[PDB]
Length: 373
Image (tube, rainbow, N blue to C red):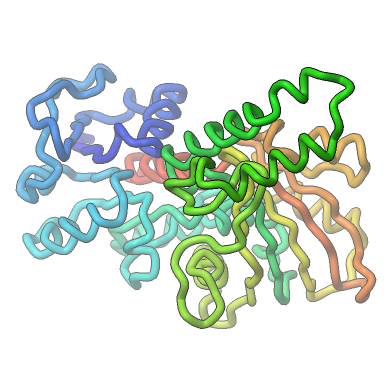
């Protein structure tokens, strides 16, 4: 009833979304003693959520961290590597709630996505698990949409072809995306304002610009605005990106199915959207069910998924980054039987990666951890 919660990386993008959400749900009213840490500004001002400690503690001081009962970090994997094992080596037996991928595949850690795996979280808490890690964006967003099928063991395999937003690469990448949009338009601003200008002239100027060294591409390396990038994260050397490899491993740990795991594969592609990830998925199901029953199973899974009837007008209104950005809704639609047989379906889902793909599972598992003491 006297728990001390420390926050690291609250000032970065993910941490800033977390703080915003915790303010919106009045989470700090449920935190007896909140503390804010810093890698740069020891003794400076903490964000004012009404907590007693108004000044920043040293994020790199393992003894200061060990004073917390719970550490909530959005600082990233390098930070986690710098202090986590040193903290545990000192005897610190508190809770580590982390956005980063460092500890995802450790046996003493749970990937928290409670609308999908609350039963797993509740069991770790009773069995002494102290590490609750946020899942990779694409998997968590996929399971928010499709958890009804997976949780019922109705999925034999799935391939997801993704349309991933810049936010997953960072604030700098989001700023570069909009800058590129502005620089593309500025090349043909006059022609666009002239209704009699030739489309092929506009077109040639834009395509020349995407191949010119004047295009702003410092962060992605290549154009994103006006283009796409069919590789995300590092090259594993087997033709697979690390983003694609996190697919099968993370999905099966969240559910608890690393014993007889479901195959999750596909291609991860960046497109010019700000912060929604979209996925076009082929699934082979273990049963030939009608679309209506599949849809009922999906709808019943959790409170945030939105099944969209498979019609044009609803699809283009509901299943887009324009609709979903900044919201907690996870629409899924285009549910159709495929030509290969009754057990093959398509699904298309859109989800905000800064919320369900990052900050939102963290505030909820913080509350669960606090509600357990």
